[PDB]
Image: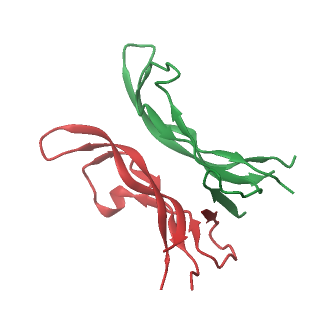
Chain colours: A red, B green
Amino acid sequence: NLGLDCDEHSSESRCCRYPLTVDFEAFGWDWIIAPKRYKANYCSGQCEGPCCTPTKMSPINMLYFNDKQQIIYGKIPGMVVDRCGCS
Amino acid sequence: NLGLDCDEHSSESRCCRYPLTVDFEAFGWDWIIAPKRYKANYCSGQCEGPCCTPTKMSPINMLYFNDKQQIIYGKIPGMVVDRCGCS
């Protein structure tokens, strides 16, 4: 398979990956220590039914408080869109 | 500029980003606690300088020992190839 990577304001119409930064403190996800922000990206474009959606995801390593007075470092899956495709 | 994202054995001749897993444990980089391996990717393909090279990079968050008996969590830049292009 083949994926496409675009900038914002590109003229590509096909299903493409675009940049997007997620900001945990902006949503009040207070229990996260780091990172406070990260580039998650997102998918958009014509698939002409099938739609443009993540076909590959990658993890990020996070430092956060849990429910049990612990601080966790852990690899959290499914956090970054690595590729977009029609499905 | 538009980037392409390939699987291994894709048959694409153009400049494209391919998957690649870096394994710190395999190279004995013993000051790194986590992650022991991660998806860095790489760039390969024809550009008809111009050479197929990374054009966007992403960090990873790492846990490691330093020179001063300390354990460090930090955002390490330039660790993941996010986009490949001809330049």
Residue at the image point whose x is 56% and y is 39% from the top: B79
Q: Which quadrant is home to the N terminus of chain A?
A: bottom right
Q: With B44 as the anchor, is A21 left or right in this view?
A: left
Q: Residue A70, relative to residue A37: is it above or below?
A: above
Residue at the image point whose x is 50% and y is 20% from the top: B29
B42 or A37: nearer the viewer: B42
Residue at the image point whose x is 43% and y is 31% from the top: B36
Residue A27 image offset from top left, x and y in percent? 32, 63
Q: Quadrant of residue A47 in the image?
A: bottom right
Q: With A33 as the anchor, is B55 left or right in this view?
A: right
Q: With B36 as the anchor, is A10 left or right in this view?
A: right
Q: Which residue is situated farthest in the left direction here?
A: A68
Residue B61 image offset from top left, x and y in percent? 44, 39
Q: Residue A33, relative to residue A41: is it above or below?
A: above
Q: Residue B76, relative to residue A16: is it above or below?
A: above
Residue at the image point whose x is 87% and y is 57% from the top: B48
A38 or B22: nearer the viewer: B22
**Number of numbered tags placed on the structure image:** 0
Residue A50 image offset from top left, x and y in percent? 49, 81
Residue B84 image offset from top left, x and y in percent? 69, 52
Q: Which residue is situated farthest in the bottom direction here?
A: A48
Q: With A1 as the anchor, is B72 left or right in this view?
A: left
B64 or A87: nearer the viewer: A87
Q: Which residue is situated farthest in the right direction here?
A: B49
